Image 1: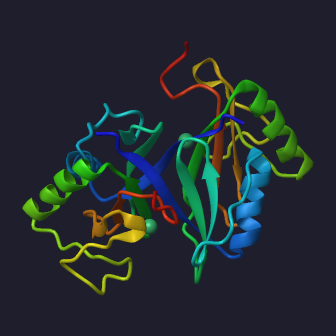
Image 2: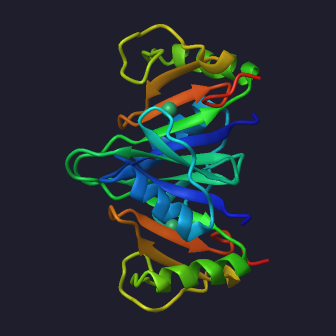
Image 3: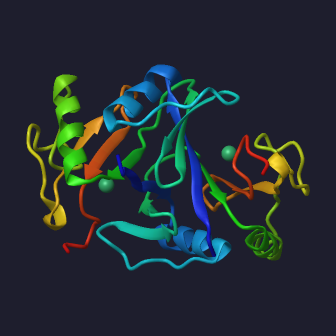
Length: 127
Length: 127
Ligand SMILES: [Fe+2]
Ligand SMILES: [Fe+2]
């Protein structure tokens, strides 16, 4: 079944600032507002649709598989933003990257506390 | 940038039952457990990784673009499960489908309250 994940909603205090944060960090573009959402289209057919939140925002986890050249570019923008990054999902190792599955990866936070991850090889792969 | 959304985490009371629920309803398969996660691979390169939750589960929204033939099949399974479905995201119209953008769509809930949506044409399209 040619099923695709088409979108998920990302709760945000400032949906426009939060969508721009993700779009800028990943080298993508923000879409025009659609209803109450600010969508960010990810190239594999799914959009992260930012919605103004009320009350506490439960942190979600969004992990992006990126090319090695994109890893270097994204990593540059993270450092330029003065953001702490971590090798590990539990944030024990700030200022380091992991090398899972022969790739490279790191975790960081968006303005709402969502846990963003970049990785260059799929979990459990290596070739 | 060939960036892909690779995975997100889905909080669940019973990660195995919840992953099986989604896999069965969409006609997909559940992957072997990886760490604490039960992944469900969606064909466009993203997995929904089910994780045992503690405390309240904040409902998330996962929308799947499906073929028209898959819509009929999935809709059949929803009815066979005795699940209420709704035309609208606010759940005002039970037992009806929407026809957004010349397609067909409906909303329903997973065992944790996550808001699942199926649609056959992308939001804002029609051709
Ligand atoms: Fe991850
Ligand atoms: Fe939706």
